Amino acid sequence: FKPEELRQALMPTLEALYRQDPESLPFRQPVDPQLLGIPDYFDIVKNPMDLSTIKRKLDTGQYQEPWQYVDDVWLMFNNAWLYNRKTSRVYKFCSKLAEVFEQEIDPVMQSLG
Ligand SMILES: Cc1noc(C)c1-c1ccc2c(c1)ncn2Cc1ccc(Cl)cc1
């Protein structure tokens, strides 16, 4: 696929995540442990990812196959589930966003091939 054609296929899945409010709000920027007052974050999460980074990569054509994008999205979720406690707001927001993502990406992927 051409860069723009793949971007157009994937973009609605990313838009769906941004549309979730308040659940996407912690995910719209890189985690900033210094500002958040959580100095253990980068001792635990070695490969950070967030929506703004995925958006930039998508908009600049860096995703050359769908699994490359899907992998980044799951990285973002898996980092949040690793770091945050199960009872925390962010963990619960992560679970909601993952459910939204599955609902959006599965039909997209089913339509590639
Ligand atoms: C995502 C994520 N994964 O682990 C942590 C910590 C975060 C996190 C937690 C709070 C964050 C954040 C990122 N970026 C900004 N904030 C503050 C904030 C808290 C709740 C809402 Cl609704 C919006 C921003």
Image (cartoon, grey):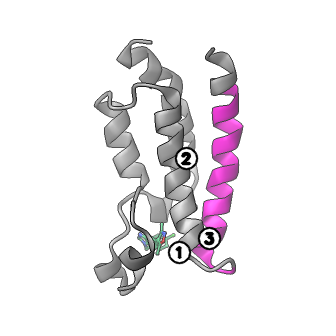
**Within-10-Å neighbours for mark 1: few <14, some 14–19, many 20+:** some
Upstream in the sequence, badge 1 or badge 2? 2
Using the rendered view, name the quadrant where residue 38 is placed: bottom left
Amino acid on which disc 2 is placed? Leu
Using the rendered view, name the quadrant where residue 46 is placed: bottom left
Mark 3 vs mark 2, foreground winner is: 3
Residue under numbered circle 3: 91
Amino acid on which disc 1 is placed? Tyr
Amino acid on which disc 3 is placed? Tyr
**Within-10-Å neighbours for mark 2: few <14, some 14–19, many 20+:** many
- The part of the chain drawn in magenta is 87-107
Give the secondary structure at mark 3. Answer: helix
**Beta carbon at label 1 within 8 Å of ligand 1:** yes
Upstream in the sequence, badge 1 or badge 3? 1
Residue in the picture at 40% in, 84% down: 40
Give the secondary structure at mark 2. Answer: helix
